Image: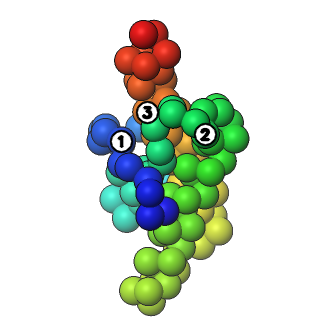
Amino acid sequence: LGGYMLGSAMSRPIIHFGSDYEDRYYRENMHRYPNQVYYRPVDEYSNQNNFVHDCVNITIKQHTVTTTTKGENFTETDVKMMERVVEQMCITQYERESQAYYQR
């Protein structure tokens, strides 16, 4: 991700999966999960979901490297959760920047 910036922080969101079980699951380990994501500005790339799938898999694959580097191993269940959280972050960043860039 050598050329990626880092957008703003936010408080932990709540991802309401469809079950209290998964809501708890996220809650247990959300402090190990990321708080921010990596992407580029709306300068050239400039898509919505096709940027989200990139920023997410950038921010998720970087975690699935550093976990293994530390000899930890967040499972594919943890990945599936963080996919959502990182999507919510990345969409929140896109929309905030949109209303400072597109709303120009």
Note whether 67 is above or below 101 in the view shown. Answer: below
| Residue that protrudes farthest toward the right in the picture | 50
Would residue 83 be visible to someone looking at this image?
A: no
Which sits in the foreground, 34 or 91?
A: 91
Task: Estimate the x, y position of residue 54 in percent, counting from the top left.
Answer: 62, 51
Q: Secondary structure at mark 2?
A: loop
Query: Can you say which quadrant of the picture contains the C terminus?
Result: top left
How dense is the environment of label 2, judged by Cα within 10 Å: few (below 14), some, or many (20 and up)? few
| Residue that protrudes farthest toward the front in the picture | 44
Task: Estimate the x, y position of residue 96 in percent, counting from the top left.
Answer: 41, 23
Structural distance between the alpha carbons of marks 2 and 1: 16 Å
Amino acid marked by disc 3 = Gln
Which colour style is shown? rainbow
Residue located 51% across and 77% down the image: 65
- Which mark, by number, is residue 78? none
Which residue in the protein does label 3 denote? 93
How dense is the environment of label 1, judged by Cα within 10 Å: few (below 14), some, or many (20 and up)? some
Verify CB contact (< 8 Å) between mark 1 and mark 3: yes
- Work out whether mark 3 precedes mark 2 in sequence or the reverse, and give the earlier one: 2
Which residue in the protein does label 2 denote? 45
Structural distance between the alpha carbons of marks 3 and 2: 15 Å
Would residue 57 be visible to someone looking at this image?
A: yes
Q: Nearer the viewer, mark 2 or mark 1?
A: 2
Verify CB contact (< 8 Å) between mark 2 and mark 1: no
Q: Secondary structure at mark 3?
A: helix
How dense is the environment of label 3, judged by Cα within 10 Å: few (below 14), some, or many (20 and up)? some
Q: Nearer the viewer, mark 3 or mark 2?
A: 2
- Which mark, by number, is residue 7? 1
Structural distance between the alpha carbons of marks 1 and 3: 6 Å
Task: Estimate the x, y position of residue 19 in percent, counting from the top left.
Answer: 62, 42
- Work out whether mark 2 precedes mark 1 in sequence or the reverse, and give the earlier one: 1
